Image 1 (cartoon, one colour):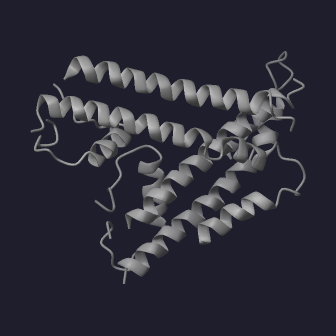
Image 2 (cartoon, chains in turn purple, green):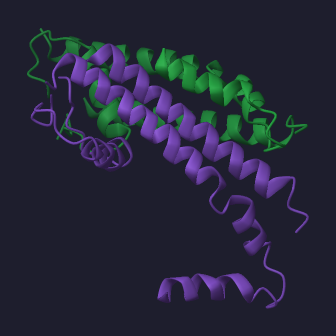
Length: 123
Length: 123
């Protein structure tokens, strides 16, 4: 509730002169792209985890039919920021999948950012 | 095929009201810049690896006429995200080459992003 109140203050008090369009950018972005990410994210995670389970999991994470959400955590941590487990040292898949997820993240971020801020602004 | 189907769903179903121009941004970007990267990437890798082989490889990676693709992996891993092997502690070359590759990555990303999203949109 505290954080909700703070973002609410960021929301309502838009009468302090014009500063671009903060709230309107919120709604135009808000959660729209975020769940699209989440969904493509989860599908990629499950897809390559399925690759591993048809390959090893009966690899990097002890290959013992373990949890998948830790794959999400790893993907966020390293392919997002850094310190991957290599995880192959498999590859035909992982390389293509990771380059694709990067390409999709790029296009989504750039397209959303540019189109929303630039044209539809009507500040 | 799973991932292909998912990106296909992202592709075809563009009739859910207007949301910028996602698919059209795909095609305008798609793979155009990606192979330009790949090619400049590979040339830089081979160039500085040739520098090393005329210098040491008969350095950081055990200098024993080893594979080059691991140089690509290293370049992606650290000069892209972090944790380089220093690799000199040579330098006249590496410093200029790396600053150049960063400059090229910048210009390509920024120019592509801005020009494509902003002007040619016709959303």
